[PDB]
Length: 330
Image (tube, rainbow, N blue to C red):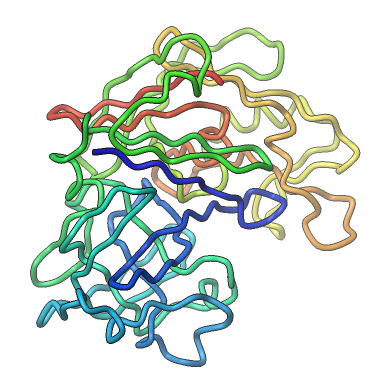
């Protein structure tokens, strides 16, 4: 089997991407944030504290003839951005782009943090990291991909995120028309539950490539590119007037700037992030100071190849017995 679904930016900055997901019988379609950095499929629901719902579409398990309470199961998650959610668990039928999993754990939120409430466009998350990170207790549950894998034509999914435009998540096949040149594959460590890999280096603009190992995670659920402070300083030094602002919480730059590209290595291959991908617009409405899309990972504890990086590539998440990651230009 295979599935193919379009993923759409939630706003003009590509702050996140949403993908429609069918849950239950009859289908209830919710727009979920596909997150290769976590492993819970959770939704706003009829059980979510009313004051914490503000415009989201909710899953109502009582209206699904295939929903079953997973007795005794609870979940609770906190994300790298400080947001969180928690609740109980149903199993139900879940379909993405024509690919159907029966008995998928659907984690129903009783509580969500303010940042979730305040984002009306995201109805929940669909985790695509390794199931070892799933938070359901006392019986850990599998991700949608993990459940679908054996049925897929090939045990893979691909992320093809757009810049200021829709893109695609495919399950079970590689669309050879969706990228240019070849796909370069690189080793993955699953030891921390992530799609963790080692970039071979970077370049800033038309500058020379610096060969250096950068361990980090491919994370579709993180907006920005978080890299070591040395690398980030080298990037922003090429932008007149750019500075790290403790008050704003990262590098900012004059909105009048033309940003240089940023290249990262995948083995001997190179992925070029155009400068415009690194512009996250005014820090506040009407400001001429703009927020940078490349930020320091210092104090995160891990480097994160978030959407800024991934949207410059066609990315293969290969869930073979020994997982790997593939990157192609597009």
